[PDB]
Length: 306
Ligand SMILES: CC1(C)C(=O)N([C@H]2CCc3c(O)cccc32)c2nc(Nc3cccc(CN4CCCC4)c3)ncc21
Image (cartoon, rainbow, N blue to C red; front, side, top):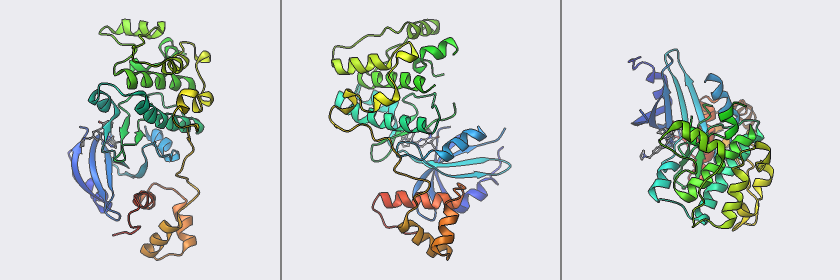
C-alpha cells in the first residue's frame, strides 16, 4: 500500500539511497559491510522464481544476497550494476567490434552455459537483462520466465536449451550490427521474418562471425549449434585459445576461511557453528553478510564489518 511501516524491518540491515526503475528499485547500503546493493521492492497485490535464484551462483549471474518478506511487502537485495543496460551500451557506440563483442559474448555464454547446467532455461535473453558492473563485466538478470525479436522460431509456432542458443544468436548479431536481424513496424510481419530465417549480413562482418551466426540462428532447433560445441567454437576461441570457462567460481559448499573468521568475531561463535550456520543458505542477513564479504574481499578491500 502507501504504508511506510514495511521499510522498518529492512532499515535494520540496510540504509536506503535513491529510487530507480519506477517493483520499485532502490539503491541501498548493507550496514554491516557498507557495500552498495539494489533492492527490488515489491508490493504483494514468482515466489518460486526466487527459489531459482537461490540455487544460481555464478560471476555473470546477478547475485541474490537477501530476501526480506513481510505480510505487506517482499524485498530482494541484489548485486547493484552501475554500468547499466547492455542495450544502452550498444546504442551508446552504434555497434561493437568483433574483438569487443567476443569479450562480451564470452561472458554471456559462460552464464547461459551455467544456468543450463543447473537445468534451467532463461527464456528471455535480451540485452535489457544484461547489465554492466563497475568492472564493466556483464551480469545476467531476469528469470521471471515477449520479447518477440528474440523469440526462437519454434516458440512462435508453439512447441528448451536450444531456444536460448537462438537468442544468444540474436544477441551476437545486435552486438556486432547495432540493429536487430529480424525487425519491423508491423508485428505480424516480424513474426513472419523470424519464422523464415533470412537476415542481412552487413559488409563489416567477418566470415567467422557469419559462420557462427549461421550455426546459432538455425530455424530448426536440432540443426542449431549445441551448448557443448559453442563453448570451444573457433570463433569463440579466436583470441583466447581456451574454451569458455563457465564453471562457477562462487560455490555453495566451499566457504571462505578469511570471511568465516571475521564473522565468528562478530557473532562470538566458533568456526564450526558459524560454518554450519552459513551453509544453510537461508538468504537471510547471514547469507547477505557472507556474500557481501566475499565481494568485499574480491575488491581486495579489508575483510572487516561495522
Ligand atoms: C535489482 C536490479 C536487478 C533491478 O531490478 N534493476 C532495475 C533497475 C533499473 C533496471 C534496468 O534499467 C534494467 C534491468 C533491471 C533494472 C537493476 N538495475 C541495476 N543497475 C542499473 C540499471 C539501469 C541503469 C543504471 C545506471 N544509471 C542509473 C543509476 C545511475 C546511472 C544502472 N542493477 C541491479 C538492478
